[PDB]
Length: 286
Length: 131
Ligand SMILES: [Mg+2]
Ligand SMILES: [Zn+2]
Ligand SMILES: [Zn+2]
Ligand SMILES: [Zn+2]
Ligand SMILES: [Zn+2]
Image (cartoon, rainbow over all chains, first blue to last red; front, top):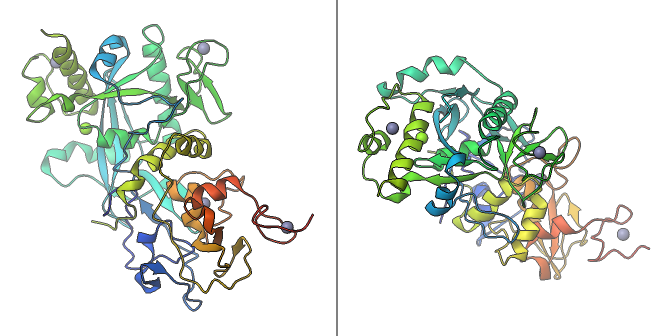
């Protein structure tokens, strides 16, 4: 059966050649027979194309020795409360040369900050995958009127991930040796993390013996929250999903069960605050 | 909307490798942990009376090997991530790739681990005969 991860979001009816397709499912039907594929010299391989590949549907259930889990139990989250950062992402929609996947528009945090990124995605070409800006539009509903202006307001992803690393470092430097991203219905937040998170075995900061907590692509090096200066990638974060603790309604509905001081000007940071707020109430009351 | 490209049996390994710093090392370490190699590749119905050389423009093969679509055997094409070439282009995409039938279980791992003779064009070890 199928999965939505890496869904081909092009509008082309056809594609792909046996040599250019990443997977058997994405071969054009002309080349399929007897459950296999066949080379047909007279059909040229497409040496121009740009196919948007969906990053929705990631699953982080790997179990490899040396590599730590991103998703952690509530108790592990309890022990690292000071590392908690609520995180929400409002998104936009692929719309011109593609349709059927969502792209990060505005990322928000428990720290009141909100950042907004240019709509960019992962586009397959005849030679490689091209990380690039792509056409997009706001979610249709009248409830999403406030992201109309955000479409114009920023910001290249190489800049966005510089600012994310700097904001968490300046927040977490004197509080913990890690992040715990506090999510609510985590799928799209996990998709955004592809844009600014690397993972591997545990590492130590060059310049330190402290746990490595950021990564730099300028040179393949690692750092702690204090020495992550100019770094662009968050390395081996941790995260929890409040919704997986049993909650019927939506985020605001379930938060307002405990707390009545967090109103909601519908900003991404406002959701991330209610996400962290509701996790504290659930975890430590009674 | 759209067209699904992949099958759930590959979700965990591709997600693991799509986030790695060193994707090739992640995949090796993943197998070493008892993980299942990447499936859903493009296997070719072919005559199996070909030259047997590693990377060709049309399917080659002997009865001792199987022919795949090159991109479907590239971990970087498979996970849609950067290639470690300075220009950043695939060696395999746009070509057919033959793989020893004994290793046809794990084509992506095979291309990660092996290398081709520039003199004679066959896989070093399966089998290049120039010294
Ligand atoms: Mg959300
Ligand atoms: Zn340090
Ligand atoms: Zn609250
Ligand atoms: Zn490739
Ligand atoms: Zn040779």
